[PDB]
Structures are given as C-alpha cells and as structure tokens.
Length: 272
Length: 17
Ligand SMILES: COc1ccc(-c2c(C(=O)NS(=O)(=O)c3ccccc3)n(Cc3cccc(C(F)(F)F)c3)c3ccccc23)cc1
Ligand SMILES: COc1ccc(-c2c(C(=O)NS(=O)(=O)c3ccccc3)n(Cc3cccc(C(F)(F)F)c3)c3ccccc23)cc1
Image (tube, rainbow over all chains, first blue to last red; front, side, top):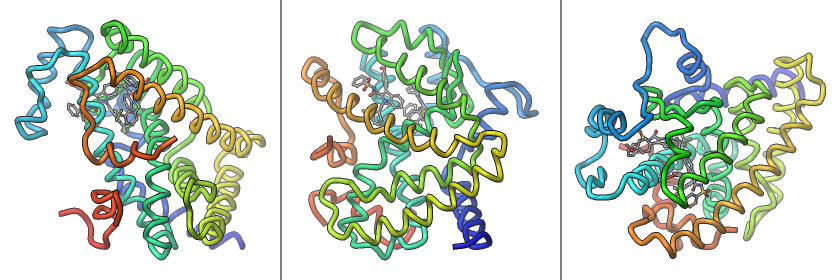
C-alpha cells in the first residue's frame, strides 16, 4: 500500500491499544512527571511505606494472592509475576485485534504469543519507569529504584537492568501511537520457533512495518533514523529475554518459595 | 490445544468475562 490504509491501520491499532491497556504511556508520563489533576502516587521507599502501600492495594486480589507470609523480596517478585500474567491477558486481547491475526493457524497464534509476550512486557515496563522508580498499581503508587536496589542478595541486583533499558528506550520519545504498532510488529514475527505457516505472518508483519515506517515519518519527522533504532531495540529485547529466562531457571533452584503462575509455566516451558 | 491450555482458552473468540 498506500497512505490512507496504513494510516487506518495505525488508527485501528491505537484505538485497540487504548481498549486493551489500562494505563497508557501518556497518562503514566503525566503521573511520573507531575501534572495531572488527579493528584499524586503513594510512594514505597522502605518497609513502613511498603506496608502502608500494601493496605491500599490488597483488595485487588483474592486473599491467597497477597502472600502475607512470605518475606518481602518474594512478595514483590510474586506481585510482579502476577502483574505480568495480567499483562499477557491484555496483550492477548490486543493481539486478537491485529487484522489477520485471528485467521492464522491457532497453533501459530499460540506460538506468536508464547514468544512475544516477554518482549512486550519489557516495552510496557519502560513506559512506567523513570530514572528514580516505577509506577505500580496502575499508576496509583511509585516504587523507588533505590528501594528495589536494596532487596536481598539475588533480587536487589536485578532491577537495575530494567532501569537502564528503560532509560535508553524512553530516550526515543515514543508515543502510544508509535508503541501500538511497534508492539503489533513484535507479535507478528515470522521467525519464532515452530511456526507452521510463516508466510501469512510475514505478510501481516510487512503491512505493520510499512505502517510503522509511515507513523514515525509523520510523528517524528526530525529523527530520520528512528525506524532503524526501533528495529535495533527489537533485537535488544530478544537478548534481554534470553538473559532473563536463563537467569530465572538458575535462580529458581535457590529460591524455593518462588512460584510461577501456571500461565507463565506454560509460557516458559519450551522458551529460549 | 497443547500444552498451552490457558493461553489457548485466552485465544478463544469471546472476550474475558
Ligand atoms: C524481587 O525483585 C524483582 C522483581 C521482579 C523482577 C522483574 C523481572 C525479572 O524476572 N528479572 S530477572 O533479572 O530476570 C530475574 C529473574 C529471576 C529472579 C529475579 C529476577 N521481570 C521480567 C519478567 C517478565 C515476565 C515475567 C516475569 C516473571 F514471571 F518471572 F515474573 C518476569 C520483571 C518484569 C516486570 C517487573 C519486574 C520484573 C526482578 C526483580
Ligand atoms: C506489594 O507488592 C507489590 C507491589 C507492587 C509491585 C509491582 C508492580 C505492580 O504494578 N504490581 S501490582 O499490580 O500493583 C500488584 C501488586 C501486588 C500483587 C500483584 C500485583 N509493578 C508494575 C509491573 C510489574 C510487572 C509487569 C508490569 C507491566 F507489564 F505492565 F509492564 C508492570 C512493578 C514493577 C517493578 C517492581 C515491582 C512492581 C509488585 C509487588
């Protein structure tokens, strides 16, 4: 194609992205930055403030999922992994809206999400982070980087990579419009392990890449290399996920008490 | 269906309820 159709694609995708993902990057940035009206996240920066915070958010999950009885490094990890599960569900509903996705072989639909969801989650996490911490509870609280950096032993070394990633990624100044298509392009990757019919996936992705190229031209006319930088980010995100999987599977042997939601167990099962 | 029972159910036409 062809301008009006690539623009109607970009628009379809943004409209779905807003229906699928509760806290947009625009609203997260408004929060992190100061503004809105609608005024000002609770901060977690020590044990006392963590416990004050947990009392604001606990109604959110049924009683067992609070894991009261676990040391805090593990509750925080359990809380992220459960928020990640909620992410997979939003991404799945997002993916279903990508023209052509639901007409793919169902087994391929599963493979695209299996291999896609972690890279997407890293991209979403970046919209919630600045140099100083991370928005939590759908933007209602803010956990400082230093607090997370002070968790015991294994855990306290492991957020800092998320932070350095986000800082470089957020320096691209992508808007939700850009992110909607960037995300759709990651999902429709034709080179995931075990795909049955690669061609119809590449064919959709080709349309998506043309919509993304047009979107960045229009929305970032002052950055001619931005498309290329974004494709490079997709490679970075693969390598980051690789690292993460390999780490999980060496840490989890030490950290009895660490448990994966079964949705994530199926995801990690043959995942590289 | 797999193997990826949950994911397969999420992929069902529908919409969470
Ligand atoms: C207790 O400290 C934490 C807590 C969470 C993480 C962390 C991590 C994290 O796992 N990073 S990590 O370096 O690979 C790591 C692995 C194993 C134990 C601790 C840390 N991730 C990535 C991610 C994406 C999808 C699914 C998951 C999992 F299922 F494993 F939870 C994790 C995050 C994504 C969002 C927010 C936080 C994270 C790292 C350290
Ligand atoms: C009190 O225990 C908590 C409180 C907050 C969080 C928490 C959270 C947070 O939002 N979690 S939360 O939904 O409020 C939650 C709290 C307690 C149990 C389950 C869920 N986040 C944001 C986050 C984590 C993983 C995935 C994403 C997304 F996919 F959108 F990108 C966003 C964190 C990020 C880094 C470190 C901690 C978190 C985790 C545990």
